[PDB]
Amino acid sequence: GSWQSYVDNQICQHVDCRLAVIAGLQDGAVWAKFEKDLPKQITQQELKTIADAIRSNPNSFLEGGIHLGGEKYICIQADNSLVRGRKGSSALCIVATNTCLLAAATVDGFPPGQLNNVVEKLGDYLKANNY
């Protein structure tokens, strides 16, 4: 039921997580998160920057990169509901639902398409439940 359970189970027991976070779109507040070994804890400021850009100008990520946990991911896909990035062999997938931002990045060497499938499936489930 809890937000932490979606992170720890639906995401992080189906992909091998470097980070996973569910946050509010309106303010970037964290609803739940998990991290392995990031240089910095993920901040509300980082999340709000991402949420604002996905809502208003997804192309901004091409110049600004995607910044989470003190790590810069390079953008490989961007629209107003789905953003993907890469930092070396770590993949990042971000979805916007009706009320939340779901972001996860996998450990080096984890298949990006597996990440994308799992994050998009949770995002669709949340949307279909009025989140």
Image (cartoon, grey):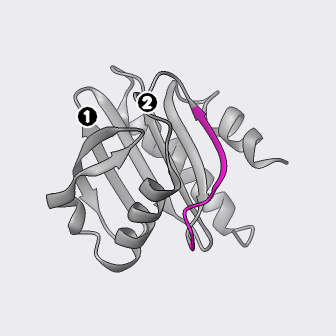
Q: Which secondary structure lies at badge 1?
A: strand
Q: Is residue 97 above or below residue 38?
A: below
From which residue to which does the magenta span run? 26-34
Q: Residue at x 27, y 42 (%)?
A: 73
Which one is in front, 129 or 44? 44
**Residue 90 drawn at (x, y percent):** 32, 30
Amino acid type assigned to the residue bearing label 1 in the image:
Lys
Q: Earlier in the sequence, mark 2 or mark 1?
A: 1
- Label 1 crowd (10 A; few <14 / some 14-19 / many >=20): some
Residue occupied by mark 2: 106
Residue occupied by mark 1: 87
Taking 42 as reference, is 12 left or right? right
Taking 129 as reference, is 118 left or right? left
**Residue 60 drawn at (x, y percent):** 22, 67
- Residue at far bottom of view: 56
Which one is in front, 94 or 128? 94
